[PDB]
Amino acid sequence: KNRAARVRVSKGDKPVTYEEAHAPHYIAHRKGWLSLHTGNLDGEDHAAERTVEDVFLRKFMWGTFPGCLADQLVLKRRGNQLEICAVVLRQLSPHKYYFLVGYSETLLSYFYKCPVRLHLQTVPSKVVYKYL
Amino acid sequence: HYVDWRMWRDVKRRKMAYEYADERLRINSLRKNTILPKILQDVADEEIAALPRDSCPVRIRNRCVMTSRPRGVKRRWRLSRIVFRHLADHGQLSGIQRATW
Amino acid sequence: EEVVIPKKKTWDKVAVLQALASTVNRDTTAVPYVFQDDPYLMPASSLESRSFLLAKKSGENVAKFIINSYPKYFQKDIAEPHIPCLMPEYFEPQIKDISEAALKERIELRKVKASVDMFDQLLQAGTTVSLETTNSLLDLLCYY
Amino acid sequence: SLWDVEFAKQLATVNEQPLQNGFEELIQWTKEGKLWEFPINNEAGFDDDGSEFHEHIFLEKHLESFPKQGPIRHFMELVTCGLSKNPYLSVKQKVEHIEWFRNYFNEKKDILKESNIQFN
Amino acid sequence: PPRRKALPPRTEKMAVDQDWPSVYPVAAPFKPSAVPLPVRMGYPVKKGVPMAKEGNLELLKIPNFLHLTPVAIKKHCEALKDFCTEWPAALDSDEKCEKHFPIEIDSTDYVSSGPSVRNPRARVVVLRVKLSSLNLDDHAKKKLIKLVGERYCKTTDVLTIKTDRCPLRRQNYDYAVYLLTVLYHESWNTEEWEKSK
Amino acid sequence: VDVPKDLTKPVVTISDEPDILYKRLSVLVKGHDKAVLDSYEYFAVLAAKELGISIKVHEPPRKIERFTLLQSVHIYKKHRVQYEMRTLYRCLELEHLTGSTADVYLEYIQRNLPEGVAMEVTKTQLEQLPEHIKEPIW
Amino acid sequence: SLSEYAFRMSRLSARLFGEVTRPTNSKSMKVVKLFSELPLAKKKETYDWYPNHHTYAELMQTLRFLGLYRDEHQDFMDEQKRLKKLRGKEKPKKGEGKRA
Ligand SMILES: [Mg+2]
Ligand SMILES: [Mg+2]
């Protein structure tokens, strides 16, 4: 039996979100993609470069915001601009959020030579789609 | 800080192949024609053989840039099949979905 | 028959953006644009507003300090056309030779202590110093 | 002068206000060069030293040292034709290839003398 | 003291009659605290309802057209109308356009995403001209057709020249014009070896 | 009440050179979402109608690129997992516009182009015969 | 195969459009082919194949030492190494040959 990115059943007290509860065969049927770019299009290029950038950005954000991210990240590219959208918690103080946001945006912009803009949506707790 | 010594050697081969690349092109141009005298072509053959081994472009292998897997790698994304499937199933690859028809 | 070709109008590279900006108007319910648009992240008072901006500026300074301290991690151009601002910053006297040209370099870099010490060493060496360079050094010392 | 530069900075400071909207941020990015200049040209910021089509293509002017007759001329005609058809190379490197062939033939003139060929 | 409490969403402060283009000036990620729309997205669970906009990652994963409302589009076009000229009235039909401008130039610009914008496909220049417009007699017409070969389509009586050797689009355009000029001049020119036809 | 009293309109300067004439502009947008393309098409059509540009929109046939990979990590060649990438095309052809109008329209649509959508714009520039080709001097 | 008029017309066309004037053979045409395209080694895909793992590792290592990046994997490795040292299994130093 397949076990690719599937959250298996449990006692029933395990909370899951919409993204992690849906199996990969539901992609483009019930849930969309976590990253949008023109690399994976007919005639376009730099698909490998976008993939490497996306992987590094997700790891960088995960380590830069420990215990903050609730769900996955939404990465968008429009021309030269890069948009990183994250759903975070509210445990940390706003001063720490603003300090990290300014530091992360500046560091990523200089590293990837493109304007990087970070947007945060704070939630009281991790949203539970269902209990598996 | 690369994945393994095999990847490190491949990087060195790519660097040494990027260097001496124009020199190989110029010498091989002499070797790949019948207009030039045969003695000059043989000298060009000796020169290109005396060139460093790692500068040969056929010693470069398209390994995975995540797990250093020498085979099962898609060239468009430069990823091994297992890493590519893992990212695709998670949904981190744009415009990639399961094929059903 | 003759066709009348209209003259080519010209505008600045930001003229369209300025026109689009003029279309929209100031909104009242919104907070200042510098802050986030999240209910938890939006400032509540003026003191919170100032503190959040200072924290964000502090983060930018920390990021800039890291970039300047470790330029080698960001020396990889991947953007075309080149973006000079998004590059590592260098503020060091690369030319270590004791000469007028390197002294002028330190004057441009605004290294007051290095420039005056180098000027003293140059004077002790006996090599001539241009009047313009001396005046430039005085301007740097007077301001700092 | 330095004082005038600082005076200009002070004038910028008193005329400087925090960004008020996304359009202003895009305008600032465009002026700073961080953002592209729409419409997209796909060639902005790239000039091959202002060279023209005749300089890029017609490279026969660089074969003056090379003999105009013989197998060497035939080989160089092939090389120049390939360089002219190449779109990924600049004029500087195209000449550099010709310079390398001229130097190589000069070094190997003795072999050419054996094969009854004269270079330069 | 208790943890900092998030303020109520500003949609409450927003009124029914509002300048929505001002609320969403540019393209921005979806914000439930700023969008006064009770939009739900997500596949419902058994005896369930689609997830609310708060914390809905699926809504965030949609490129929103809030900044492109019809009112905003009309206002933006009205401001940008000052930047546009008027097409000539005499060139009413394509026949008149062909009559006054026999030469047509085709080039392609590509819009991509990423730090780099360079694209080698932007150097291709296509020049189309009908040989009927060109001042060609019998000898020049026949010689030009033989020289160009497959570059000329007899059914459309159109000569098409594609230039991609030059690195720059302007250089390709200059080379294309130069090729057309030399082809025309050489076609009109008569050579002695042509007598052996 | 707190509205700006005066607004500084962007400066538009008319040069002395004739504007470039474009016979037809073919704007082809590639994407993975048909609804996004439909929304972008409606936005582009509305903008063209407001600016008075004649525009025709049609849907080129879609392309699907499929490939297969091993389902497992070892000794399971028989079982495969198949992936695909769907590229949907939408072509908007605008005719009888000048260079200035085309430049403004392109800049407006490109800035409003959503993420994950590629645009290819094909030009059709009208030109006269060159001076050298006017008459057979040779 | 072709008449003299056709041959000279074809040669004139080759001169006009930039092709090789002389009647070369297939082997000799490789000289034109080699210089008409970038070498595979010189292509950007070849040398810029791997990302700079030295940069992507040292930069994160510097950030972690500066207290701006938390690595769960590195914390796991450090904790396991500390526990092994407490248990007794410590890494032998270079030049300390247990078997020697
Ligand atoms: Mg099975
Ligand atoms: Mg191999």
Image: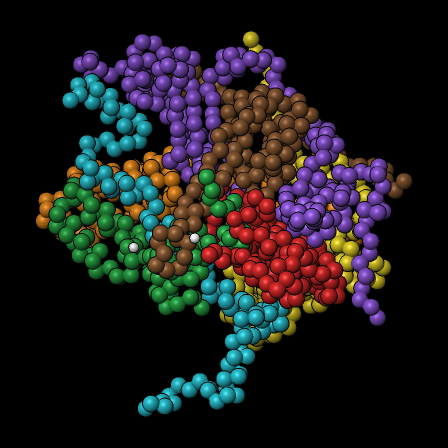
Residue occupying the point 37% across, 88% down: G95
- Residue E37 visible in image: yes
Question: On the picture, is E176 further left or further right than C96?
Answer: left
Q: What is the letter of the orange chain?
A: D
Q: Which residue: 24% across, 59% down?
A: B51
Chain given the colour cyan: G
Please name the color used to draw chain F: brown
Residue B11 at x, y percent in the picture: 37, 61
Seen in the image, is B78 located left or right of residue B94? Answer: left
Please name the color used to draw chain C: yellow
Task: Name the outermost residue toward the right.
Answer: F1
Q: Position of residue C142 (x, y in %)?
A: 72, 66
Kindly identify the residue that appears in the image at 47 percent across and 22 percent down. Answer: E104
Chain letter for red? A
As drawn, C137 above or below A115: below
Shade representing chain E: purple
